[PDB]
DNA sequence: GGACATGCCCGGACATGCCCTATATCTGACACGTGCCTGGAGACTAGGGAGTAATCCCCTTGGCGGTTAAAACGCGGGGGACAGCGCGTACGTGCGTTTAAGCGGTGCTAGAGCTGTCTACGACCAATTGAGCGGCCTCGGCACCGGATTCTCAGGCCTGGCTCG
DNA sequence: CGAGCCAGGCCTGAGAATCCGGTGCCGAGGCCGCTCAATTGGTCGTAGACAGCTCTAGCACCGCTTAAACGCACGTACGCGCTGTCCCCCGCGTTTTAACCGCCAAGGGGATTACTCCCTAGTCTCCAGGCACGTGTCAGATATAGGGCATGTCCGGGCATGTCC
């Protein structure tokens, strides 16, 4: 019997091809499912996770902070135009809001 | 009853402050109370409907998450 | 004479303070009593999970913050600073909630 | 011992260690990541199912998945995702 | 000879039941077909999700009823539930 | 002889057709017998209400045939139908003749 | 000769065009615009008649609604004349801007 | 290749659209923004429509493609198919 | 101070087009007849998912208290909400023109739509085990509290030049 | 010329960001045990890729007519700016009060496991009604004509203040 090696490893991915496949199969989406669909899904989810984690890490280091916290996730999403667009209708718990003051509210000399 | 006064004036001021407003009219408070109450009515209606369909007697966090999702604002952090 | 800041300075200071942090601003227990009273008008003797009230409270504060952001923007459009009920009504009418 | 509850915690951690070896993750943040991944999953799978139905297609393939990804993701994100998906699928098929 | 799917004869019978003096144009009939199909899709989809969330694999009348209660406004929901219950009871007795 | 479930139930929409469309939409693996009957009954109710209002509007316009304009009037004048169809655009429907009070002459 | 007061004819046109239902945007320039935009996304597209009519109905409904909201914001500001800032406010509050 | 047909979206047409919306007075400067807005709308719809057209191995945009595109952008349209 | 006559303003009497009402024609779009065949209706079988009974423990509900940060109230005030007025400038409204919008007819072929075959692709089931999830430890990153520090800012003392007798 | 009083400038008195530091703490990361589902393997239905044919209308062209766009002239109504007012909310201070954490009892139902049962997928067979096709036919678009009234405009009555005897 051949040594068992995982599909994620075969694809160079970290997300589970088998698990994503089972959830896709059992999500009542279709009776027949292709082999490449879970590969694509795992690749897109890993890519998006990698980009969000990059921005959140950047924000954390800018704050001299070593662990990603929800505040850093909220800052990372809102500070990128495309992530903010994708997640326009998403509220992050414990995320707060962007520091931003309208020009008219600032004091004048 | 009298619990509508538990959303206290400094609390509405603080929520409004996070919204970025600098000055708050005295008539704002009643308006905020009304808007919040209507919002709650709709959310709680949906939540209790879900609880009753499942033959439960306690509103769960997941019921609330579904109510919020179907209301058009998805909330992350309590499951799902 | 005792020190006194001109109107606005403390408003900006509190704006910065509450926009920098994320801890919840509405009191938990009065909201909980309100939610159970309102809920009882729909189904009697209903129960609530703790995490359910916390979810409802997070949602409420996010909704109010967004509504107040839009109200402030509409007020500024009218070369005003102080928000008034008609501003709330305009914001909600244009959002499509009325 | 409770019932089997599926989650992606270990895979998110593996990707994080790939992209940021010295960075951790909190439980709240992991919950936010799980909500995000599940949401994207639901969106893509639903759009792909609808696409397949519209064209009288009874089998789920990779073309509808790719088109759904292109519809939901912005420009450069779609191009990068498509490149990764094609390379990964062709490499898998080689095995 | 390409068979299609429409409710034309049934809409016409209901119209004759309520007003046996009025006609209907092609554009109005198209709007009625779009409307009925849209309502159908909304109610069936909500019922399907409801059933999935509670670990139910069969579409029965209780989930349909709850979905109707969620989607229809007050008086509309009450009248629809009353008519549905009377009709289902008459059918079940008639077998 | 063959007699249909709609006939036994006294309804106008076809139980069989609604059943086929629910079954073939890939919605669920089993389907109850009462669900399509209930659905047909609700659809009938809503059709009867919309045609009632549209007929009324047509008669108010001295028209014997309902047109899309009358459908738009019916949907937008009824508070609950307007709520149900808040995000719905009806072709050739136009808008309600609504003029703001402040815009009227003095 | 005779000259109508400013405002009466505007209102007359409002009533006229709100009473009837014919399309108000010209078919041919809209079709030409559609073809120009389509050219930059995919080459040599062909369009159904009912497809261009669909785009035109959707566009006219969208613009009518946007102008309604713009008018409401202008009157809210004690104005009658619509301004670019009014359009921008309406679109920002609607959430598309 | 059609060029500079943007001038075909005329000023009086936009005026009539505003009349149907209940607008009594229209600034002369409104039109270019409106034209831009109109263009933006088209850019979204056509991208989805052509995508559907391209997915189905078709090269001619159909009414059903457009209705589905409009529906999936939340602006569902009645009268051209369900 | 009383009488007089008119200037002026506002509420009733007026010639053009817009709204409303009446009616002939048709015509093509709406209502009705037909064949059939594919989906709907009657019937038998199975099995697995749904209905129902017993447990529990954990997850919620209920209660006392303290005390302190938050809530309720008093009050000065000043800056923003609101009313009033000028203007001029860009927009409402009228008219000639051309410019193209809109309708009728035909091309025909690219491209949408219906059908034939079958072989790759995916549903479906047995055994397995290794990845995936529940439970426990811990220590380090995070949370809470005390500490010195500077900074953009305010105030008092000294200097200097203007003014009056 | 001498004394006076203040404007103004510069060198010491100040509530929040600069960290700076320390200590506790609790929960995520790792490890281990259990466990259940993805694999691998194989077989068989099946459906959609590709060919092939048909046939629909999209595109282009031509022609014509006529409503609309555009440019210009002109009057004008209010957006913006400015000024004045006022009122009522921000900020601070004082008193209150319940929020929240702490702790402990108790019960009830969500979920689990097991047993049963009945309801619909599946298949078969037969039949009926819904949809192209066709055809009759009639209500609104188009067109013309007639009544009546809104409107920017005019006129008469009442009010008011100026003037003479």
Image (tube, coloured by chain):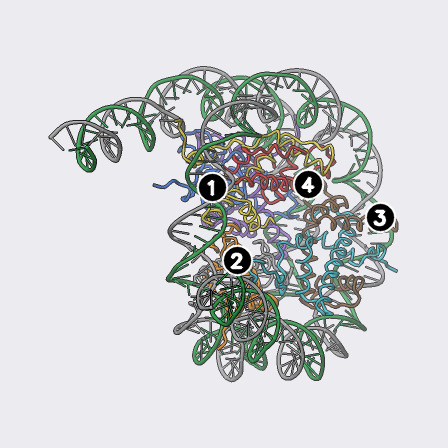
Chain colours: A blue, B red, C yellow, D purple, E brown, F cyan, G orange, I green
Tag 3: Cα neighbours inside 10 Å, few (<14), some, or many (≥20)?
Answer: some
Chain of the residue under label 4: B
Q: Which residue is mark 1?
A: A78
Query: In what element is the residue under mark 3?
Result: helix
Rendering coords of residue E49 (x, y %): 67, 44
Give the label on residue E89, or none: 3
Discs 4, 3: same chain: no
Task: Say which of marks 4 and 3 sits in front.
Answer: 4
**Real-space CA distance between mark 4 and mark 2, rounded to the nearest whole angstrom:** 35 Å
Rendering coords of residue A107 (x, y %): 38, 40
Give the label on residue G71, or none: 2
Query: In what element is the residue under mark 1?
Result: helix
**Real-space CA distance between mark 4 and mark 3, rounded to the nearest whole angstrom:** 28 Å
Residue E39 or B7: which is nearer the viewer? B7
Residue contact between numbered discs 3 and 1, judged by CB atoms under 8 Å: no
Rendering coords of residue B49 (x, y %): 71, 40
Chain of the residue under label 2: G
Rendering coords of residue D43 (x, y %): 58, 46
């Amino acid at each position: 019997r051949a040594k068992a090696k995982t599909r994620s490893s075969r694809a160079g991915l970290q997300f589970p091809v088998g698990r994503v496949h089972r959830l896709l199969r059992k999500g009542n989406y279709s009776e027949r499912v292709g082999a490449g669909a879970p590969v694509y899904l795992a690749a897109v989810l890993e890519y998006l996770t990698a980009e969000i984690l990059e921005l959140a890490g950047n924000a954390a280091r800018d704050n001299k902070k070593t662990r990603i916290i929800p505040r850093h996730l909220q800052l990372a999403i809102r500070n990128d135009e495309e992530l903010n667009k994708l997640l326009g209708r998403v509220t992050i718990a414990q995320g707060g809001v962007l520091p931003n003051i309208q020009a008219v509210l600032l004091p004048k000399k | 009853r009298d619990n509508i006064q538990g959303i206290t004036k400094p609390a509405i001021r603080r929520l409004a402050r996070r919204g970025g407003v600098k000055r708050i009219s005295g008539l704002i408070y009643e308006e905020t109370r009304g808007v919040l109450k209507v919002f709650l009515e709709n959310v709680i209606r949906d939540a209790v409907t879900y609880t009753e369909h499942a033959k439960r007697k306690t509103v769960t966090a997941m019921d609330v998450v579904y109510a919020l999702k179907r209301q058009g604002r998805t909330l992350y952090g309590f499951g799902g | 004479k005792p020190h006194r800041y001109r109107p606005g300075t403390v408003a900006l200071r509190e704006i910065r303070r509450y926009q920098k942090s994320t801890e919840l601003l509405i009191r938990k227990l009065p909201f909980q009593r309100l939610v159970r009273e309102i809920a009882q008008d729909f189904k009697t003797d209903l129960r609530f999970q703790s995490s359910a009230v916390m979810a409802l409270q997070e949602a409420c504060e996010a909704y109010l913050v967004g509504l107040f952001e839009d109200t402030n923007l509409c007020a500024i459009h009218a070369k005003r600073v102080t928000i008034m009920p008609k501003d709330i009504q305009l914001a909600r009418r244009i959002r499509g909630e009325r | 011992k409770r019932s089997r509850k599926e989650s992606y915690s270990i895979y998110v951690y593996k990707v994080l260690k790939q992209v940021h070896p010295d960075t951790g993750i909190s439980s709240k943040a992991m919950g936010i990541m799980n909500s995000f991944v599940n949401d994207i999953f639901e969106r893509i799978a639903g759009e792909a199912s609808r696409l397949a139905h519209y064209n009288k297609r009874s089998t789920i393939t990779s073309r509808e998945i790719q088109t759904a990804v292109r519809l939901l993701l912005p420009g450069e994100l779609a191009k990068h995702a498509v490149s990764e998906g094609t390379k990964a699928v062709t490499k898998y098929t080689s095995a």
